[PDB]
Amino acid sequence: AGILFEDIFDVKDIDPEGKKFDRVSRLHCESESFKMDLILDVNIQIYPVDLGDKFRLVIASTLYEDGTLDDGEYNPTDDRPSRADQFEYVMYGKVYRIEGDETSTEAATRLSAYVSYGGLLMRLQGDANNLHGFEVDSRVYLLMKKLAF
Amino acid sequence: KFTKRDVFLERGEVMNLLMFLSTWDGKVPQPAILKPRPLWTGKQIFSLIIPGHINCIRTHSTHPDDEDSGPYKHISPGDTKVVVENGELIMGILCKKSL
Amino acid sequence: DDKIHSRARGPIQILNRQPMEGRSRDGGLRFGEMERDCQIAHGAAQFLRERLFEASDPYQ
Amino acid sequence: PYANQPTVRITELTDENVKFIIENTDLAVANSIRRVFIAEVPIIAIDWVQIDANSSVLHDEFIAHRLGLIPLTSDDIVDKLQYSRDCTCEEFCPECSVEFTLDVRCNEDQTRHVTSRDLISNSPRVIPVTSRQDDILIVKLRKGQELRLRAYAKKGFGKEHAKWNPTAGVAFEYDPDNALRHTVYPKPEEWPKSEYSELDEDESQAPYDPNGKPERFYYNVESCGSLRPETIVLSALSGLKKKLSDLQTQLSHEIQSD
Amino acid sequence: KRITTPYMTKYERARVLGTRALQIAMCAPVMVELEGETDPLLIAMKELKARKIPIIIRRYLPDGSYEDWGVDELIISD
Amino acid sequence: EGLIDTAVKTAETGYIQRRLIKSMESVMVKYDATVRNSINQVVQLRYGEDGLAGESVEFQNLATLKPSNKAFEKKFRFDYTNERALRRTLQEDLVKDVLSNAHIQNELEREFERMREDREVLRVIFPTGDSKVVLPCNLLRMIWNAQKIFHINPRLPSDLHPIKVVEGVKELSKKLVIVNGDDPLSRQAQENATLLFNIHLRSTLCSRRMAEEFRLSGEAFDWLLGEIESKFNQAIAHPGEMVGALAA
Amino acid sequence: MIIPVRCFTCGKIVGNKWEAYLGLLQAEYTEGDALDALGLKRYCCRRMLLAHVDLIEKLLNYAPLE
Amino acid sequence: MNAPPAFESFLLFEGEKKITINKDTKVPNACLFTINKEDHTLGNIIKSQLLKDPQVLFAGYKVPHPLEHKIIIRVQTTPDYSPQEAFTNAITDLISELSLLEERFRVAIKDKQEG
Ligand SMILES: [Zn+2]
Ligand SMILES: [Zn+2]
């Protein structure tokens, strides 16, 4: 499987502090079921998004259904099934910091996965239950698809 | 300007730039954005230029001081707070402070 | 072309048997005292002695 | 995994320049054809001047310099002659060169204007641009001076020297509306519309187009007077084809040898 | 009872490489199998890496005494 | 005005530099690991009062300098009473050992006492609380590299007993030598020279910080010690280096 | 000293136009009009007729003989 | 005084090969084609044509030094398609495209004149 996280979200604010760049903007999105924050950074130029739009974000450790754990290299000449066939915006990054509300005695209750898609940042803040599949220094994908609803 | 967040390159440009690399291992890195079109990012290409597994932290010239104290410390809207791990650029924009 | 210059055991002076001076007279560059101090800083004593004795004015 | 089917359409055909459009081709091919238009175009020109008596006021080499820049019509002679380097004889043979002569001496009181018309060529078709508009002024002589010499012309291309540069200025342009965003205008309203812009006067630039390749390359090859524009284009295409054929032959030999 | 540092300083390494290169250039026997090279300096570098240079360094002390160290005895920096 | 200033500077600085170079042109570091001059007169028993090359030195900070007495206690003491914290940081097969065994507790208490002594020394030596100091080995970078190589994953309970850290630090404090010799004067000089570096080493590597912020494992800590010793050895000042010209 | 044969930047022949340029300027035309009357569109070729200095005349004043 | 002549940019010197094949060792099915006495004109079109072919995983040229007249083309295809045949096919189809373009331009010209 390799589905490290799966949940629907909705856009609620874009670049609150003013659009800094010209092709990237902040998406301060929220969830609908797990109630988790989202600070994804998508390429607004090629994949435009407006407020109120919902999308199915799915952090997956691999793009194959069988889950063969690809090494990581651009090999377009590949006929194997790919989960990207049903997503309009896919990215590839490497989580680099898992901050949480830990203490000296009792375990953390809310984590915060910080993943960098080669420059595009994303903070999946929420409870510490559904973020068990995130470990520092590990490759991950995005696999988001806008919902027509 | 090459290491800003809003830098995207196509396969042709990436493959053209890799030719000017005297230490390329010969493997094309996974693009940062597979669909709807394979687009690399300036930081991702610059990572291959960094040799070995280097780790260092530096601050950009236009880094607002009232940012570390408040939230968004590890995720900076202005793309500052250079962070390199295993010799791969992750955040920040390179300037004289880092190069 | 008016500034480019080189040398390889060119003519020597008459008073002190050292190379000439000036592009027109086909002379060598001066290895100033500051260059000597820099070479001492590098600790390259052999290179220093070569520049000051071997390729300057050997004599017995 | 093969080539494409480009199309051509001439918009203006004159005896001084041509404006054609090439559609359905890659940008690299267009730029390469441009660089061939400027550099690798066989053409005849002056390259060997023997000055016997030059009493003018200018330098001895100045005359040769000016003579080197005088275009020579080679509509049907450049394709016949061979490069002097690859000749199989001695001295500039007429089969691989064209001889010229100039003998002017100001005798009257008024000053002379030694123009290109004084270059008496042995061949009929290889003459400076004076057939059909003043002539290229070489030098000015005064009563008492003279200029006797004879020069030979040979085949060459712009890559060797600018004398063999037939095209005056190639106006290469594609995607008039900044649709592929290959250039980002900080203030689009401040820029004028391109000559080939189909966009109305209201909008500043066409909208973005993610899945869009460069096509419809516009050209404005402007002949200096030596070779006809369409002739320049045909020669460039044939020469590029020849270079590819030679490269292919060399590659085949190298592979076979291994 | 040697008290000098057990590491080879850069100065000593450079001088040893140069002297061995000079000796090799003067038709002297090598102390390592040649893989097909000819530059004497490269051969000297290979010998230094292989720790087979037949040279011993005499480090003079300020007082006047000295210590004889062999290239195959102390650790090489680079 | 600016042009005149530049002209006079271009004429005066040359003479200044010439006089500076002609006064320390024979000073050097002999093989006796000491700086002298042409007359063999000792000017410094160790180059730069430490005997280290100026190339391999980087700016760092002193964690145990300018803290608060209450903060200093809760960052370098390694409380061995709260068993929950130990289970969170160390593994189960170490919490019982650190609880039952009293020798480990006494050793850790001695470590904290030595840390306090070093803090007092720093305070009496570096007045005005200047944490920014220059030392050979950048321990934070080394720890980070170890974490990134061995994949420490600072969330799980690490397997690194505090006694291992204490003994490793003591041995590394012995391996790094500057004034060779077992003579009491030799040992006193060795302790004096390599004093600030040892204080920094102890302050960064502790039983609490190592088990709370770094979480290094045994192999990682051993690799760290090897790297530190090798880098310090390379940082030593090469005898025969003309330091006078460099200073000028 | 003398009008060049071709424009340095573009390459178009401009040597055969100095006399025509002077004639047009003499008759009634101005510079801004004469330049485009001769057929000079690009601004790079227009400097050859505006910037050029005609020093060959002063040289001819020093006639060698007679 | 040391300015090189103008014929050393296109004319071959005695002993220099026009093209040399050299296999790479870092990855399988990868060769570097070194061309002598050429410029971007004859390498950019080949780069693009190779990019068109889907079986070519990598393709791009360079100029080791502008003053030196030399270009290196690195090609890497799938394991079941050697780069030599890729280069040959790129040249062949590019030549065919240029010939067809020439023919179309010629017919367009002959029709433009009085037509
Ligand atoms: Zn002939
Ligand atoms: Zn012009």
Image (cartoon, helix red, strand yellow):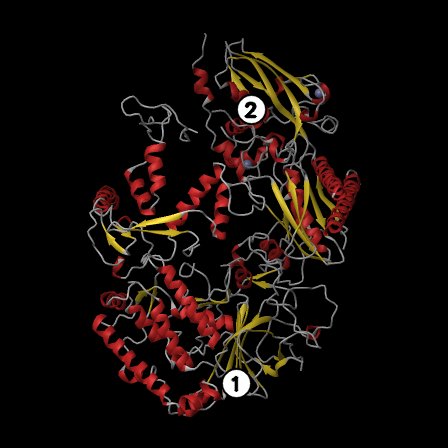
Residue A23 location in percent, x, y?
55, 66
* Nearer-the-camera pick, D33 or H114: D33
Q: Which residue is mark 2?
A: D66
* Nearer-the-camera pick, D229 or E31: E31
> How far apart, in angstroms, are the residues tagged by discs 2 and 1?
80 Å
Residue D41 location in percent, x, y?
67, 34
Queried on whether the Cβ of the residue with tag 2 lies below 8 angstroms from ligand 2, the answer reads: no
Asked whether residue D123 is in view, the answer is: no
Q: Which residue is mark 1?
A: A126
Residue A133 location in percent, x, y?
58, 81
Q: Is residue E51 left or right of residue F169?
A: right
Q: Chain of mark 1?
A: A
State which quarter of the image contains the N terminus of chain D: bottom right
Q: Is residue D61 left or right of residue F111?
A: right
The disc labelled 1 sits on which kind of residue? Gly
Q: Is residue F108 left or right of residue G60?
A: left
Q: Is residue F190 above or below residue H102?
A: below
Residue at the image position 74 percent from the left and 53 percent from the top: H82
* Nearer-the-camera pick, B44 or F89: F89
Q: Is residue D8 above or below residue D231?
A: below
- Mark 1 nearby-residue class (10 Å; few <14, some 14–19, many ≥20): many
* Nearer-the-camera pick, A18 or D188: A18
Task: Provide the secondary structure element on which disc 2 rests.
Answer: helix
> Which quadrant of the figure shows ligand 1?
top right
